[PDB]
Every structure is written in structure tokens, then in C-alpha cells.
Length: 286
Length: 285
Ligand SMILES: CN1c2c(nc(N)[nH]c2=O)NC[C@@H]1CNc1ccc(C(=O)N[C@@H](CCC(=O)O)C(=O)O)cc1
Ligand SMILES: CN1c2c(nc(N)[nH]c2=O)NC[C@@H]1CNc1ccc(C(=O)N[C@@H](CCC(=O)O)C(=O)O)cc1
Ligand SMILES: CN1c2c(nc(N)[nH]c2=O)NC[C@@H]1CNc1ccc(C(=O)N[C@@H](CCC(=O)O)C(=O)O)cc1
Ligand SMILES: CN1c2c(nc(N)[nH]c2=O)NC[C@@H]1CNc1ccc(C(=O)N[C@@H](CCC(=O)O)C(=O)O)cc1
Image (cartoon, rainbow over all chains, first blue to last red; front, side, top):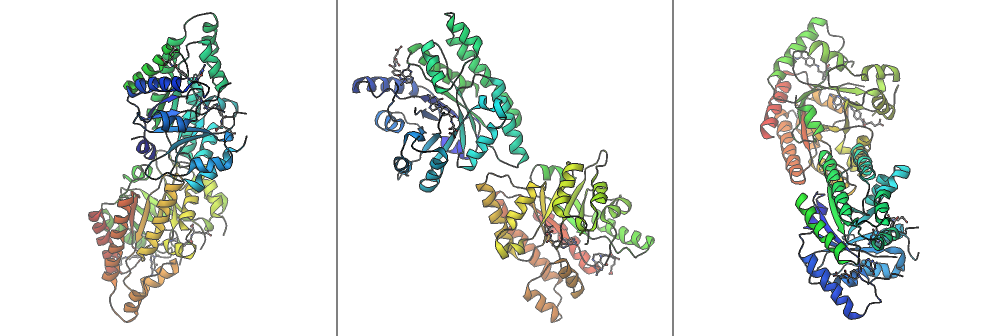
């Protein structure tokens, strides 16, 4: 389902996204956390499950978390790799094809390293041409030099067949990126790959500082409301939905294949329950 | 008539008929008679467009022929230009758009007053809405296997379709199509319509002209001709067979394919064979 959507460059891809727990936790806490992820996510209708990688918070390896903890979830997993964490020989090994299974992955370069991103892309070309590779796109970064479309075209050239954005909190940056992506592709006679927009609810100052650490900002107006002790969680979701709806419209008009990834980044029941509900609402919309 | 939409929609099924304007030396009444015969036969065709060749013998200018003798034919005209015969300034003048009217042109380089690369830049500057096509030569693919790259590069410079020279070798054409398809698939490119030219050959006179244009027929075919056999039908039959094979290959891979039936002969029998073939190809596609 997911593999085909991606190979045929279709709209409508929908994924949910989680970060594995800390390594620190007892072996029993993990299985509980893990069984909770399984119960709620198995209740969705998604094409795949993104599992993030971070580069004090050291989380379970995304692929190990996938295989050894989440096998009961019968959907593909998109395994993120902060390649700079891996020596080039670890990276060759992790990228090897395994007989009788597909593989989905997003290679993430340095936010600011034992292995550079250009090198990781060629290591993949060497060892597993069939790995369904995605790239990270950052619409906010397009405001600074109007070349994030060019950055993702260079990633397409390097093997990428889809892009998953960080959390989108600004519709104009996102439409500006989509625009320059559409027009450049058209002018250079290119086909387009799926642009998967991530939505990430934010319901506490705790969630927010994790988000800032990931490089995600929310609007100053919204943060202001949080620092002045209002509940922003529902305004998160409403603003996120608003944004995605406008992007889905912009994308229909121009035939840009668009997907959505609903990211759950909080340790709080209420916020996690908001993510799950957002993931259901998004399916309904598209 | 649907021609622009088929081009812009990258559709299969473009069919055109192809003529070279008569010699410049014939008289205004004789050009009018030649032109009346053309309009008579070609108006009996269901085609998308009439290709009008430019030679780099001296023949009436194709745009001038189209506009002042072929008004009666209600179909778009694809104006060939051997850019090398025109100065950079005269080319600007001819490229300029005409109000409420689509322009179609194939720019041909040298086998010169203007380089082809500069002719493309002139189109970019003076008329971006000119529906521009390129010559593709499958036979030449067998030299270095890079004709597909030649055309990709022409697409980059503004071409939106390709009209090959007369096809007589199905394997070279299929090799060119194959590499075009696969290179397009792997570098994320859309494909543009490849219009294959079929050109009946009925006499040594037709052949010497075709040879001068850079076209060859198969040795076995030319052998029968030089041994005084009528090859007109054989050349048509072969042309049809090649195109059926190319259509099948193209349909399987989703490659947009068209056909241009070229008449290149002064002999009535060869001209009627070309008309017939045009109607045959339409039926086939
Ligand atoms: C998307 N990220 C992310 C996550 N985990 C969660 N939960 N959420 C996230 O958004 N883990 C990986 C990354 C963490 N943050 C970031 C943010 C930006 C870049 C970044 O600028 N990436 C460029 C690299 C530039 C380079 O060195 O070439 C890239 O294209 O990958 C990397 C990591
Ligand atoms: C490393 N992670 C992490 C983070 N954010 C913070 N602040 N801390 C973290 O350790 N973001 C990503 C990931 C999330 N980790 C976890 C760990 C446990 C539970 C968990 O115990 N879930 C219960 C708790 C309900 C509640 O506390 O309200 C559940 O019901 O789902 C959730 C996410
Ligand atoms: C297609 N041609 C043609 C015609 N007229 C008729 N009737 N039939 C034809 O096939 N007029 C123009 C051209 C004459 N023959 C030729 C054959 C090859 C090239 C050629 O190789 N063209 C390259 C140019 C490369 C360069 O400029 O170096 C091209 O891309 O156009 C040009 C003219
Ligand atoms: C410059 N041209 C030309 C050539 N080939 C040769 N050898 N000489 C040429 O001058 N090929 C292309 C173009 C064709 N010119 C012409 C000129 C006149 C008629 C013509 O009078 N057609 C009549 C004659 C029929 C007959 O001779 O039996 C007709 O019935 O259509 C056709 C093509």
C-alpha cells in the first residue's frame, strides 16, 4: 500500500509518527509504553508508522524498537537515521538488504559527526538501491534563500522518493515551498514526489521545549498564550488542521501529491490522545 | 486541430502529413496548380497538422508557402527552419508571435549564419509560446548510443516534441525509444511525443533526394530497385510494419507516439501511395 503510493507518486499517503522511549527505563516500562503505542495506533487507518531517531535523551534504536517491540503492528515502519551517529561500517551493515522484506527509511543529516549525509546517500546507492528512501524538508528554511525546493531536488537526485517535513506551523512558508517546487519541476520537465506534511500537536511547555530542541518553532502568539497559562493543545490541533486543509487545496489545484504524517512527541496522555484523534480526523479529510 | 492539445497533453496519436514546398523557379500559376493538387489530396485526410519542410535546389519559404497558398487547408502547419540560412535578426522577425494564433516550428541545425543553440535562445526571448520541436535521428543512436541524450537536451532548450527523419530500421528506433524511456524513468523526467516519419520510396529519383536529406533505405530494398523492380509497395509495407512494431512497443511502456507521413516525390504514383499510407496509419491508430 505505502510502497505503491510512493512508487506511483500518489496523493493520500498518511502516516503516524512516534519517538521510541529512553534506554534508561526498566525493561518493564518499555513493554508497557510499547503496548500502549500498539493499542492506540492499531486503532488507526494509516499507511505506515514513522519511527524517529535523535542525535539527556538517548532513545531505543528505531529499528530495534520496531523489530523487538512493535511487531504486533502490521504496517510498514519508516525508520529514521541520524546518519552522523553511525560509523560508516555500522551504516553499511544497517543498510544491507534483508531477504524477503521491504525497507523504508529517512536519512537525516546534521542539525548544526562520524558520517556525513552525502556519504550516507552513496553508501545506500552501493548496498541497497531498493531501500525506499525519503528526505527531511524544512519549509521554514525556504524563507531564508528560496532554495529548499532546490535542496529537495538534489535529494531526489541522490535517491529520495518522498519527503517528510518537520512539523508545519506556518502555511505561507509551506505554500511558498510547494510553489517553488511545483514551478521548478514544471519548468525542468520533472515528475513530482509525495510531499508528506507532518502535524504535531503541542499542549504543554514540556512538549514545546522538546519541539524547540528538534528545531520546531510554534507561532509567537501561540507560545504567548502558553506562557500566560492557557491550554493551547486544542488550538494546536485546530491550527494544524487549518494549515493542512489549505495545503491540500493548494495541492489539488496543481496536482502536487501530498501526504500527512501525524507526529506524537509528548509523554502526556492527553496530548497523545490528541495526536491519535488528529490522525483519525486527517484520514476523514483526505 | 487537436494538435496543440495533444502536444501539451503529451498524448499519443499525433498524426501529420509532410510536404516540401515546390521549387522557387516555377511560375505563380504553376505554384498555384501544385498548391491546388496539395490542398485537393490533403483535405481528404484526417490529420492533426501539415508539416512543411525547409531545405538548407531552392524551394519556397515554408511559412510563406503555408500562409499565401495553403489558407484553404483548415489545419495547423508545422514550419521547419534550417536555422543556419537565417541571420540572427531575420530569425527574431520570423519568430515573433502573431496575435490570436498558435505557431508550430521545428528548428533544424547543420548537417551557417545562426547556431542552433542561439536559435533556441532567440525563441526563449522572442516567443516562449512557440510550440517547438526537434529532429531526432534514430540511425545515429547506433554510433554512440546518445541520441536519447541529444533529445533530452533539446527538451531542456524548449522542445516539446520530436519528429524523426524517415524510419527504415525498427531496431535503431526501438533502441532509441528504449534508452529514452529508461533514462526518463531514472532521472524523473516526463516524456514528450516522438513522432516517427514514414516516407515511401518509389524510384531512384526519390531515393537520391532522400539520400541528399541524409536518409537511407535498407540495402536489400535498394538492391531490388537497382535491379529494376518496383519497390514502392514494399517501402510502404515495410514502413507500416515498422510503425506497428513501434506503436506496440510504445503502448506497452506508455511512450507517447505519433506519426508523420512524408511525401517527398514529384511522381503522382508515389504521392498517391503517401496519401493512402496517411489514411492507413490513421485507421491503425
Ligand atoms: C526531523 N527530526 C525530527 C526527529 N525526531 C522527531 N521526533 N521529530 C523531528 O522533527 N529526529 C530527526 C530530526 C531532528 N532535527 C533535525 C532538524 C533539522 C535537521 C537538518 O537540518 N537536516 C538536514 C541536514 C543538512 C546537512 O547536513 O546536509 C537534512 O536534509 O537532513 C536535522 C535534524
Ligand atoms: C523519549 N521520549 C520523550 C519525549 N518527550 C519527553 N519529555 N521525554 C521523553 O522521554 N518525546 C519522545 C519520547 C516519548 N516517550 C514516551 C515515554 C513514555 C510514555 C508513556 O508512559 N505513555 C503513557 C503515559 C500517560 C501520561 O503520563 O499521561 C500513556 O498512557 O501513553 C510516552 C512517551
Ligand atoms: C530533417 N530534414 C528534412 C528536410 N526536408 C525533408 N523533406 N525531409 C527531411 O527529412 N529538411 C531538413 C532536414 C534535412 N536533413 C538534415 C538531416 C540531419 C540534420 C541534423 O543532423 N540536424 C541536427 C543538427 C546538429 C548540428 O547542428 O550540429 C539537429 O539537431 O537539428 C539536419 C538536416
Ligand atoms: C522541391 N521538391 C522537389 C522534390 N523532388 C524533386 N526531384 N524535385 C523537386 O523540385 N521533392 C520535394 C518538392 C516537391 N515538389 C513538387 C513539385 C510539383 C509537383 C506536381 O506538379 N505534382 C503533380 C504531378 C504528378 C506527376 O508528375 O505525375 C500532381 O499530380 O500532384 C509535386 C511536387
